[PDB]
Image (cartoon, rainbow, N blue to C red):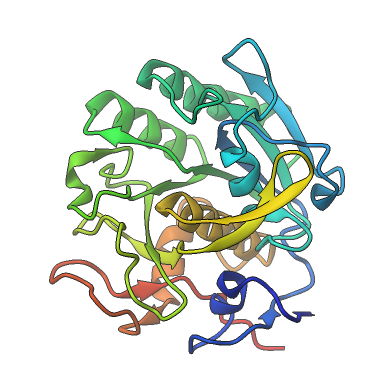
Amino acid sequence: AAQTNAPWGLARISSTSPGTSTYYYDESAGQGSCVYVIDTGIEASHPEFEGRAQMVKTYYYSSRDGNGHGTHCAGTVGSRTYGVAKKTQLFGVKVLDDNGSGQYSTIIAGMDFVASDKNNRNCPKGVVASLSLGGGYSSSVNSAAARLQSSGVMVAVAAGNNNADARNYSPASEPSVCTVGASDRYDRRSSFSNYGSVLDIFGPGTDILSTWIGGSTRSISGTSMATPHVAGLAAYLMTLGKTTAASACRYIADTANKGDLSNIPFGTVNLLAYNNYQA
């Protein structure tokens, strides 16, 4: 399939070079897979989700995305226009309040919830979790992410937006999950993106157009935006049966565009998510 005048990020992950505007992808489009967006929630009524989005859990007085951050990330995973896996199933887990903040205890509870909840859901092609969140180093938060991964979920987490080594951030620094840094449309590392040995992969994260609350759209930036590109790509590749939850991160690094990014610090991978779609 082909989506013309797609967001640059979607175009980027199906091309070997920056600067194109068409998103090429297999038409299966992540159908049969499920992605848990662990974030501020999801405006499931947004037309862009086509009914493929639903809340399954909240930790606050409301299930509503009163912020937009989660709706935006969810949109990059699987919205019709702005999503990588346009037929995936989307599950919202609201661990972050309407200011985009959350306690570690909640976030941990959230991961544990997803590890169990996937057993209530029909996801024949496998399960992904996208975590565009994180703060300082936490052993307990890292362990939570590792449990989720171990439970049979493809876990993708943001590297952080501190322009620093992600070794000092969680769940970014958990070795066994997929840690995602951010790039811009010129294949530069995003100015804010964390780096470091713990990163597994880069995805588009500067100026990313996706869904927003009130049935709208907007373009924002962050490793939070890069993460769901990789989560969506996981779900997409899993649906194609090219890889599994356990190996998806490795497979994405295996098949990534290599050495194409600039301002990558020594000891940080130069790999950019890529679907290697050949019609």
Q: Which residue occupies the foreground of this view, 16 or 188? A: 188
- Count numbered badges in the picture: 0
- The x and y percentages for residue 60 are 58, 13
Residue under the image location 31 percent in, 44 percent down: 172
Looking at the rendered image, the quarter that the C terminus falls into is bottom right
Q: Is residue 30 left or right of residue 224?
A: right
Q: Which residue occupies the foreground of this view, 8 or 54? A: 8
Residue under the image location 47 percent in, 53 percent down: 227
Q: Is residue 181 left or right of residue 113?
A: left
Task: Classify 262 as above or below 52.
Answer: below
Check the image and name the residue furthest to the left.
Answer: 266
Task: Classify 141 as above or below 30.
Answer: above
- The x and y percentages for residue 193 are 31, 58
Q: Is residue 173 left or right of residue 68?
A: left
Residue under the image location 62 percent in, 47 percent down: 72
- The x and y percentages for residue 80 are 79, 60
